[PDB]
Amino acid sequence: SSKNLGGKSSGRRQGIKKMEGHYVHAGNIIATQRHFR
Amino acid sequence: GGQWRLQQGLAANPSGYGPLTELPDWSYADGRPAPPMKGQLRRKAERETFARRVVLLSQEMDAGLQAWQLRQQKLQEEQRKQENALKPKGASL
Amino acid sequence: VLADLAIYEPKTFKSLAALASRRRHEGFAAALGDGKEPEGIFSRVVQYH
Amino acid sequence: KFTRSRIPEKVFQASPEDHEKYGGDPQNPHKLHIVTRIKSTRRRPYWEKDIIKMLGLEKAHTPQVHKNIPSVNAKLKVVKHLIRIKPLKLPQGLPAEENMSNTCLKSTGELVVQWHLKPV
Amino acid sequence: VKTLLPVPSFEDVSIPEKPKLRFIERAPLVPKVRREPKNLSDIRGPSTEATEFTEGNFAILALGGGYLHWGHFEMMRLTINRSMDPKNMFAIWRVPAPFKPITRKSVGHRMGGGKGAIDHYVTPVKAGRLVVEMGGRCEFEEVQGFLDQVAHKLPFAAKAVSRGTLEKMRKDQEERERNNQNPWTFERIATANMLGIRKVLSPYDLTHKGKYWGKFYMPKRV
Amino acid sequence: GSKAVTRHRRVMHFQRQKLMAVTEYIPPKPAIHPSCLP
Ligand SMILES: [Mg+2]
Ligand SMILES: [Mg+2]
Ligand SMILES: [Zn+2]
């Protein structure tokens, strides 16, 4: 009766913050990731 | 009902767009015309603003076409001025 | 006014029924002939401009 | 899942049979549309409601004129199933300053520049 | 007199050894331990694999989706084994052994508490897929008899087809598709989103084109 | 509600039923029936 337990971790909100063409000041984070994309 | 009325160009509902609607309903006994009916004045104002929009859209489209013609001609003349810059001397003799 | 003509003026309603039946017959003969010649008589709508 | 429909672009390419069936001419295309709203935005998604509000078609059976350019053609392609598009053709010229009060729309899309109320 | 004709001779067909159907086991020899969800889209729409003939000339053609479990495999192999001629015919399985696990909770159980335990193994079959293929030095008629007899008892609709009958059916379906007289197809209305009709359709209906509905196949639909 | 795939033919939405009613195969009609012609 629910032998499996643990996978309740939420999403990391990682991805591209600034796409192509967006003006970016110095120090703005462009993309968050794991496992280099 | 009328959908035969559309084939004669007559706006299927006979109580709009005709002489049955747009003519004045009454007049005085000595011959003087009536003041204009209020729905007639509203329809005439709406027809005027529709025609104004038609004129404005056609003029904006023609002005856009003429400005694009001038942009193409000016770019082509500027590049033709760019082509002729030669004063060549290297392999001539 | 068609119902009021039906009740109070039956001669005018017989005239209207004769008109509708004649235009029906003209439409039928126009359907058999595609016109050619006359497109009837009680056809030929009056044109307003 | 239900999502917005992108349409293949081979739909909006007229065949010569289509040019014979309808009246249009592939050279000299018409300049203006006459769009009329003939189906409710209710029980349709919110993007179709927004496009209908943008184009100016809130009141049904009320004609509105637009340009014939690819941007408004994209907006009309989104809601082409709620409308009736017919070309504004002009029998006389487009209306001058003297005419403007005396004009009419005349279904069959003929913006007649002289509108009397007398028989021919 | 009555005109006799040359028979179709068979000197180009060699029957292989082991001409009868092999045994099909109930469960794979390595039992699967992780329960899989009910991916119902393996019985849905047209088949993409096992669609054309390989060795024989005769087949059972599936005309709708369905899951074959071990009872259907036993029925098919028993009937085709006992009703063929082993010295002139041979049959070939065109479906793999049943591999998809299906779990049932215990009898009379409340809802909740996780998935059940794996009981029995099935194999999905889509529409248009061939199921058994037969060949040999025989005609179409006798195998049409005992293959319609088998194909009646499958969980979906099925027919016994030959190469000629399948190719005739495909040409006739395409000729019906190009002879159509009303201008409104399901394809033209579905892909172009006429009438806003994509609200009541599926995203799968742009490829199914109205010929498919659930696990069912309507072969007159065009 | 039921799944997308069912066992019992799954009665359609009425707009889809109208769509499948209006797009049926219509066979070509010869002018004179071919046997009635020599
Ligand atoms: Mg997770
Ligand atoms: Mg969470
Ligand atoms: Zn006959």
Image: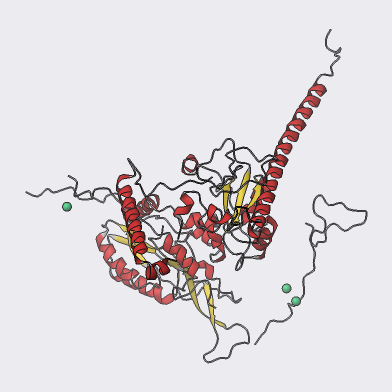
- The image quadrant where one finds the C terminus of chain C is top right
- The image quadrant where one finds the N terminus of chain C is bottom left
How far across and how far down the image is residue D42, in percent? Answer: 61, 68
Most extreme residue toward the left is E1
* Quarter residue E25 falls in: bottom left
In the displayed structure image, the side of residue D67 where residue B93 appears, left or right = right
In the displayed structure image, the side of residue D118 where residue D68 appears, left or right = right
Q: Is residue E13 above or below residue B69?
A: below
In the displayed structure image, the side of residue F10 where residue B26 appears, left or right = right
Foreground residue among D55 and E32: D55
Q: Is residue F35 above or below residue D52?
A: above
How far across and how far down the image is residue F5, in percent? Answer: 50, 72
How far across and how far down the image is residue E69, in percent? Answer: 44, 75
Most extreme residue toward the front is B30
Residue at the spot 38% in from the left edge and 74% down from the top edge:
E74
Foreground residue among E55 and C11: C11
Residue at the spot 84% in from the left edge and 16% down from the top edge:
B86
Disc tally is 0
Q: Is residue E94 visible?
A: no
Foreground residue among E143 and E196: E196
Q: Is residue E129 above or below residue C25?
A: below
How far across and how far down the image is residue D116, in percent? Answer: 58, 45
Foreground residue among C18 and D70: C18
Residue at the spot 56% in from the left edge and 61% down from the top edge:
E196
